[PDB]
Amino acid sequence: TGIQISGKGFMPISIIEGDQHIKVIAWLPGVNKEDIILNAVGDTLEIRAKRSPLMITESERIIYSEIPEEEEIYRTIKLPATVKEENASAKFENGVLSVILPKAESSIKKGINIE
Amino acid sequence: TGIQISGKGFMPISIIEGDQHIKVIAWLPGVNKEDIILNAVGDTLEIRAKRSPLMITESERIIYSEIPEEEEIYRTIKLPATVKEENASAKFENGVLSVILPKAESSIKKGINIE
Amino acid sequence: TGIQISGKGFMPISIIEGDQHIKVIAWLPGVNKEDIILNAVGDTLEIRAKRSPLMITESERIIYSEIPEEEEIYRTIKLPATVKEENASAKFENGVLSVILPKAESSIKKGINIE
Amino acid sequence: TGIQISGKGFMPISIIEGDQHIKVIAWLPGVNKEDIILNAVGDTLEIRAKRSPLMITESERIIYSEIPEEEEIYRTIKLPATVKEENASAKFENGVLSVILPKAESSIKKGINIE
Amino acid sequence: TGIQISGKGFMPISIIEGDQHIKVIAWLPGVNKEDIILNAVGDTLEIRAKRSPLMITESERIIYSEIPEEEEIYRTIKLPATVKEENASAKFENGVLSVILPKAESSIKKGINIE
Amino acid sequence: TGIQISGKGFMPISIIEGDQHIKVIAWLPGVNKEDIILNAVGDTLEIRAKRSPLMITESERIIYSEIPEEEEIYRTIKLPATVKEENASAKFENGVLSVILPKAESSIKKGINIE
Amino acid sequence: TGIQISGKGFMPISIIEGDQHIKVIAWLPGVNKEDIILNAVGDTLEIRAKRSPLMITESERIIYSEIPEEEEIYRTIKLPATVKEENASAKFENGVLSVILPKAESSIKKGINIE
Amino acid sequence: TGIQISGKGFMPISIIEGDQHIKVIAWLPGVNKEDIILNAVGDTLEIRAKRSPLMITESERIIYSEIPEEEEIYRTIKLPATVKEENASAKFENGVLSVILPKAESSIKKGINIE
Amino acid sequence: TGIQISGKGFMPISIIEGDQHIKVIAWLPGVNKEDIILNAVGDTLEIRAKRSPLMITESERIIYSEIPEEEEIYRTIKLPATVKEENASAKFENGVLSVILPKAESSIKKGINIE
Amino acid sequence: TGIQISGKGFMPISIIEGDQHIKVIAWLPGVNKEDIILNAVGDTLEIRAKRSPLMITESERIIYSEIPEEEEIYRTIKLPATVKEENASAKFENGVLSVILPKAESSIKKGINIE
Amino acid sequence: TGIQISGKGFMPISIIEGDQHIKVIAWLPGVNKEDIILNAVGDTLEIRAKRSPLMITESERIIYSEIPEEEEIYRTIKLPATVKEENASAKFENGVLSVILPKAESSIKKGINIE
Amino acid sequence: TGIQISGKGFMPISIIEGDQHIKVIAWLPGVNKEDIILNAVGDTLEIRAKRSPLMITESERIIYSEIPEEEEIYRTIKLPATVKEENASAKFENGVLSVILPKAESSIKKGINIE
Amino acid sequence: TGIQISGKGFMPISIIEGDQHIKVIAWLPGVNKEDIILNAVGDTLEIRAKRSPLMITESERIIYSEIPEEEEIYRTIKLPATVKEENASAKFENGVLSVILPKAESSIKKGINIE
Amino acid sequence: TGIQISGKGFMPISIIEGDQHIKVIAWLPGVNKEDIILNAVGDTLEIRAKRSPLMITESERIIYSEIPEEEEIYRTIKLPATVKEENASAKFENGVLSVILPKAESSIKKGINIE
Amino acid sequence: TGIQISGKGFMPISIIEGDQHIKVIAWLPGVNKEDIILNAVGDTLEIRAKRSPLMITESERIIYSEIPEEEEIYRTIKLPATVKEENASAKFENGVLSVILPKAESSIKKGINIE
Amino acid sequence: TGIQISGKGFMPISIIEGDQHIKVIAWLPGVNKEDIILNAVGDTLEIRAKRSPLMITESERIIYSEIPEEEEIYRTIKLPATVKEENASAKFENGVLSVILPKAESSIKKGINIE
């Protein structure tokens, strides 16, 4: 549907497009700020992250779990437009990752009169 | 299977039992530290929480998303054994919740080494 | 579903639990002020009521009817928590009964600090 | 069966035909006096009403309810005979509406007796 | 059999259609000459009758009965074609009614005038 | 579909609408002027016909034939609007029947404008 | 079956063979005499025709038809025996075509004596 | 509903009804004000119109289209109530048609007050 | 098929190509001239629109509709060639949108001689 | 098998093919010389006959019978090669018909040498 | 279907039938004028042709194709009529083959007058 | 496919045509030159043969055998053209039979020049 | 399969790609020299043509045709590499269309040393 | 899934990406070093090879084989990034091909800060 | 088929058989000579080996593969003839393995030369 | 599967084959070291033992038990190859038996000359 996505593991994401930039939304619970790698260029975006396994005491044991445990996970997406990555910015809080990607000049759409 | 869990929406949770305590783990992405209500007595656990919606500018618009949008979500659990909630504790970081539940000394089993 | 309900006839009912009280609703069309029996104890609730049959003039005849004709009906309910029925209150209007059940101090959940 | 009924939502109704009139019964739980609209002409009758769902207070946690809650509801009925609407009458108490309409055909009362 | 007959009580009827009229034979045992109400309009016919009440008593221990005293009995017949009610005629003998419905002039089917 | 047709035998037909009339067409292969029946009233039409069977000489024998053998054929049709059958006309040539049905003025729907 | 038929369009036909000739029957609703071209040689017959389409008025519209639309139609049939086309004859009436085919002398059956 | 709809081709429709009138909504994309034929009488509606096909130059060609090409299209409607066609009005804008149908005096229903 | 389309809601569209320009065809019933936003660049065409809700008087109600009720709708198209947006023009009438996009020289085809 | 046999009734037959002629055998028990009709031309043959029923005196009764009762019987046969029916010779004796038919010159097969 | 067609390979063909002749149309793409062998007699036509394989350069490999490859191709057709080959003619250009077959006199059909 | 074959026994065959002749091929294993009979005329071919059974010694017995043992066998064929049998020649060696049939003058086709 | 082909109508095309150029091969039988339009740029190439219909005299008609009749046809293709149209060359004979595309500089692939 | 591969024959492959380059893996059994051609450019890479067929001795026979027989084979793959072919390197050992594609500058990804 | 093979792992194989020896072919991509385990005796042969997995640098990642990842593989074969295993020989070049098995003189078959 | 197993009682067993020996494992819960009988010869192995029953004290009484009570238990296993039982060994700990079966030296497979 105008975009392609790939990667390993589970990863909720969402994308918002403006007239000058694009906002990226991602869910990465249980990760330390340093465990994240995000690289981009042109119109392509890459997300890489690793989470610690849930340690347990020798006396302790798990009766039940829902959480997938695979530590390494990443997701790749092709955007609908080219961006100026060098000016991009991102915020991460509450296990959630936030990104801002300025649009490239060529991508800036233009209006047309209607009569 | 000896315990039951209930609630609305999508919410990962994990449960672990210790000799002196029981440990509960849950993922609360998009929840501010103060947005959480957590209540416990005896051997039953309850959780309620609200995550802000995805804000957008009139120019901006959502193109793709799998993340569910509903804000308020909750979870309820019945433990297998009684706990001393008065001494329990909870720690929440990076959109993930952990809770320490002291087992009742009456509930605390007596491992015997014999042969 | 964690609670049980039974009885005879059609008597739509809905239950709402509040931190300090429980609100319950029952559809009772066409029933007079004197026909209603209410009883609650511990964490269970009972209702019994009787509606006069459809009287008609000798020259009249019922050509069509979807309204059920039975007079007496009752319903049993298991509450999830104990209530202080002695201080409860209820009201009936427009064929519907409204109830408020104060919750016992023992049953009232305790909140725990988050850190 | 010589008479037709239609509308939306749940609305039990009873039709009673007299030698000089037709009486109609409608169950409208929780419906206020001013919210109900009654209209008729010829040999057809129509009903409109709307019910306010509820108000939230405190936690306001409700389990799977047995009571329906569609707000707007109406019903239309074709009578077997023409009625004199200008002389009709209606009353609503205990959540049930009662209506009596004199029959225009009865005001004519044709007869061509032969051997 | 493509035509509708309805009513209450036991009242055998035979409907005969002519090219200029409709003739109907009906069984009305025990009904007086003045007790038979006959009405017609458009393409429908109404037959109404009442027989002697023939009450019940005691000190007899009724030993046998096949004759019902049901007084008010009627039948509604959907005629296949329009009739001129003002010109109808009938004869009643030995509890059997012989009606004539002269639909002789209310329409005249087109004919062959081909050239 | 707003008009109904039935009958026995093979009889193709087609229907037309006119501003002040209705045209109807019927294929009647091998039918003589005298074998034909056409009657109509109101908004319904009837057709009956009978065609002589396949005659054969004593010295001849039918080695193959696909043409049906039945002689009598007929059709009945419900028209969509009222017609003034007294003014109708029809023509039959080359085994095909054409009929002209002037429409009832009351049935004519004209005289609405846009602004 | 010792004989073949082919062509396009709707064309009922029946064939009858005489000891000295062969007679053929054809259904041609709505065809003008000149519209048809019948030819023959050897033991095969060819029939060509064209039926005018259903002309219409500007205000007119066709609401339904059973009649097929195509105009140009023809059929071909291979006779089992040779004929003397120069002596053939045909008659067409009431949208129906008849043909008489004198059988060739060698085509005409010869009977061996009793012994 | 008591209403019927018919016609050919693609023509989206919606129908509103008023107490004193009836309002009709029709989509007619790609139409000029003069191409539309509408007429009304009694309690039934008809709408007929024509839209030009897609013009093109010999140096241009169709690569992809969803819009159906057939030009002549119409629809018909059977109302549940009679209207006063002579007083009806209609407006057309932005490819959409709005019609106002003053309801007949007999059609106008009588409201019934609750006693 | 070498061209990509996307958006939300119902939006008929068709596309035409010439040697020097691109023509765009779309259906927007019931929209006001200003309610539409269209931008494009490179080979990408964006269409955005918001439609008025079907106004209804309090006494009225929609007995039936086919028109989709959603108000805002938009579409995106990736053309097979590049365009000079700054020179484009568009006309809109009768609920239809017309847009002409001159092709970009670099993308503009060249004729190739054949010998 | 390159040839066809047809007819009615029990008529066993056998066919014998020579270099210069064809001989054919047919079982016709109980048929008179005057009852037989045989006709052949080209490379096909016809046989027609009739056998009288079994007579008995009125006092006599058939205690056992396997012999068939039907009288009229016939057969038709297609040869694989043309025959000169002029020179045909037939012999009927003991309820069996024998016939020899010289073959046509073209039918006559020339012996071909081996080198 | 009155004519037989056979042969190996791909060779589109169509047949035309003159009253004095027969014209045949065949597609023989990629063939040099001399590479066709054609011969015919009676009412049967034989066509033989061979094409060079689609040559390739030593440093050339085919990415994609659909054209069938077999070099020799032939077809045979049995006409419904006898012809005079000695007088025939044919043309071949633009990879398309044309042939003219004058009919035999016996092939000439004789028109039949109709009465 | 325009050619038909018949006979009894096992006899694989293949057929060859040239511009000047026809060549025929047959497998007749275990058959001596003297046991073969072949005949032909016009455009049809006959084959007849008989193979000596396998003799067996008294001390010897057949353990297993796939070979069909029927001695006499024959085949019949209809050629696609007429031949001149008086000049035929055939070879039989290595258990395989070959035949060369010079064409008839009508059989040899005449080339048609191209324009 | 990594390459795009498109267009309407019947147009066989086989594509071949050389290291230094692209050769394009297509079958366009039955078209005139000038009705061929081939244009290209970048990495995409277009083909348009029209073919005369099979004309006939009124005395003439058809027995059978395999050739499709539609007249306008075209095809478009996206090559794997960009070209320099200016040096393009093409030949068309015998209904076969040949085109040569010298490859663009940036497209010329470079061999890699092997170890 | 973002990468495309095509070709004919059997040739297992696998692909790897690095931050400076791309590594390619391929199985090529039975290939001498000389018969493999590798070329690539930009983001396009092609592999061509031909293997000697399995020669055999006159006395020899193939009883069973799994290996496919085709000799010429190739593959094409379009990479996710463009490379600097001139710097590439490819090691071939043990019937397996290894290739190194140093990434081009614009392909080089850029990391972006987070807070 | 009288010969069987078994084992785990992917290993295409083809058996060849001489008169004085037997040849066999095995595909073993990525198998170092030292990882090769092959053993046989009498008329049965064994094959076993392990392949190193594809290593990667931490920065590197697998995007797509077809390579089978199982390492340890082997095969077992029953040969149809005994061999002098002590006299066998093998060759392993470019990932393809070949072997020669001198056949035991007992297995060696003695030719028979008679007419 | 080349080996056979038999015996009585509950006895999980595992079999492992090496290059020069064969290893066998058996579960012997509750069996004393001396309770076992172990014998083997050629390529078959025998194991027999008797395990004591479940004793109970005077005051005791058995309420539940799953363990089978049968004392005598044995198993018979025919090995695939002959073994050097004279050199075999066995080891039994924690109720589980292990046995080493050095297989016959003659069974060794060797002889292939590795280049």
Image: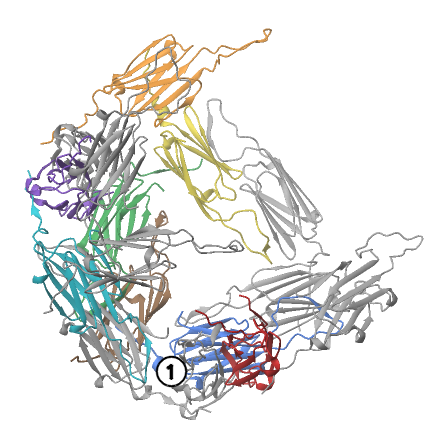
Chain colours: A blue, D yellow, E orange, G purple, H green, I brown, K cyan, O red
Indicate the quadrant containing the N terminus of chain D: top left, top right, bottom left or bottom right. top left
Percent position of residue I100, x then y: 23, 72
Q: Is residue A53 visible?
A: yes
Q: In the image, is I106 to the left or to the right of K94? A: right
Residue wearing tag 1: A104
Give the camera-side residue of I44 and E88. I44
Q: Quadrant of the C terminus of chain D?
A: top left
Q: Quadrant of residue A44?
A: bottom left
Picture coordinates of residue K61 (x, y %)? 33, 80
> How many C-alpha atoms fall within 10 Å of the one at disc 1: few (<14), some, or many (≥20)?
some
- Left or right of residue K36, residue O104 in this image: right
Q: Mark 1 belongs to which subunit?
A: A
Could you tell whether O26 is left or right of G81 in the image? right
The amino acid type of the residue labelled 1 equals: Ala
Q: Residue K33: x, y in percent?
A: 15, 73
Q: Nearer the viewer, residue H80 or D24?
A: H80
Q: Is residue E26 left or right of residue O111?
A: left
Residue at position x 8%, y 41% from top?
A: G33
In this view, A42 is above or below H43:
below
Most foreground residue, D24 or O71: O71
- Is residue H72 or residue G94 the one in the foreground? G94
Residue A30 visible in the picture: no
Position of H87 relative to E61 (above/below): below
As drawn, I46 above or below D49: below
x, y percentage for residue G73? 16, 47
Residue at disc 1, secondary structure:
loop
Position above or below: O84 against H33: below
Q: How many marks?
A: 1
